[PDB]
Image (cartoon, rainbow, N blue to C red; front, side, top):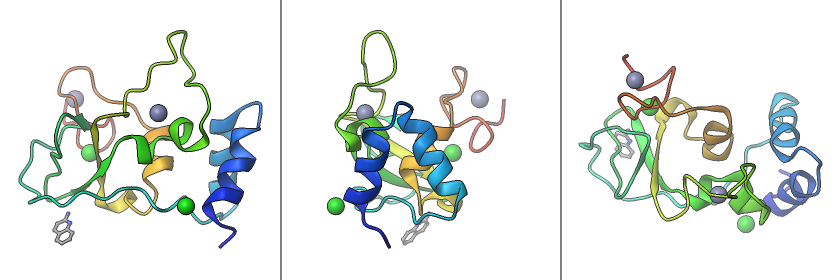
Length: 124
Ligand SMILES: Nc1ccc2ccccc2n1
Ligand SMILES: [Cl-]
Ligand SMILES: [Cl-]
Ligand SMILES: [Zn+2]
Ligand SMILES: [Zn+2]
């Protein structure tokens, strides 16, 4: 209820933007909205980050940059290269977590074997 710009400004200027958003969520803060939801059939591979939407029946698909805290905050990505894994791609979010795609991508890691989210889609 505070608004996306209010939350994103708070996280953007924090020394640790990821910790700012995680602590905000843990405090009961309403997730960031206005992520770009994709029209899909839910018959996809269910892999986490894809060239085209790949949601299975347990997922929703979103535009990648819209679900990236660093993209949404207009700040550098936290790696030497400043590379973004999500920009220009589509991200599959478990339906149970799809009320907060930005928090989900921030908190989770892609399985290097099967390419699905560890602890969710991944069955390795
Ligand atoms: N995951 C999933 C399955 C079926 C849907 C139907 C309509 C909207 C969203 C859906 N999501
Ligand atoms: Cl907005
Ligand atoms: Cl998943
Ligand atoms: Zn990004
Ligand atoms: Zn796996």
